[PDB]
């Protein structure tokens, strides 16, 4: 003799020892990224090609 | 006679029960099961 069993309810596991099907469908995906940058240029110049006489002292 | 018509007794009350079932034996006046899946499932 087994216990009371419902009629219209689905067959769910209810006690220790009942079986149940697992459908393994796992799909995980993670990601990350980053960056950084910096820059600097400089260029100076000056040239007195032909100096007049009254400025030759400087 | 009269007091029983005016009062109730503490601890003497009613409760409600609900359930799901199927009714068979209809003359073709049942569900159109193509739109009530729980009928065929149960």
Image (cartoon, coloured by chain):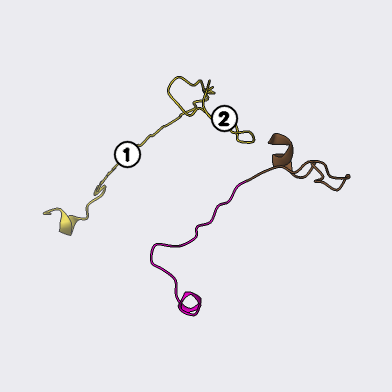
Chain colours: A yellow, B brown
Residue A58 lies in what quarter of the image?
bottom left
On whether residue B11 falls in the magenta region, the answer is yes
Q: Up-down: is A49 above or below B3?
A: above
Q: Nearer the viewer, residue B20 or B31?
A: B20
Furthest-front residue in this view = B1
| Left or right: A57 in relation to B5 | left
Where residue A5 is drawn, which disc sits there? 2
Furthest-right residue in this view = B27
Query: Magenta stretch?
Result: B1-19
Q: Nearer the viewer, residue A48 or A41?
A: A41
Tell me the element at label 2: loop
Q: Residue at x 86, y 48 (%)?
A: B29
For mark 1, what is the residue?
Answer: A37
| Chain under disc 2 | A
| Chain under disc 1 | A
Residue A27: give x, y in percent of width and height: 49, 27
Q: Residue at x 58, y 29 (%)?
A: A11
């Amino acid at each position: 003799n087994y216990g009371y069993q419902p009629l219209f309810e689905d067959r769910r596991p209810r006690n220790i020892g009942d079986t149940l099907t697992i459908v393994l469908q796992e799909n995980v995906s993670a990601s990350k990224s980053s960056s950084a940058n910096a820059s600097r240029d400089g260029k100076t110049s000056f040239g007195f090609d032909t100096v007049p006489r009254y400025l030759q002292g400087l | 006679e009269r007091i029983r018509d005016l009062t109730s007794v503490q601890g003497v009350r009613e409760n409600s029960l609900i359930g799901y079932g199927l009714v068979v034996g209809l003359d073709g006046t049942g569900d159109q099961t193509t739109q009530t899946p729980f009928t065929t499932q149960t």
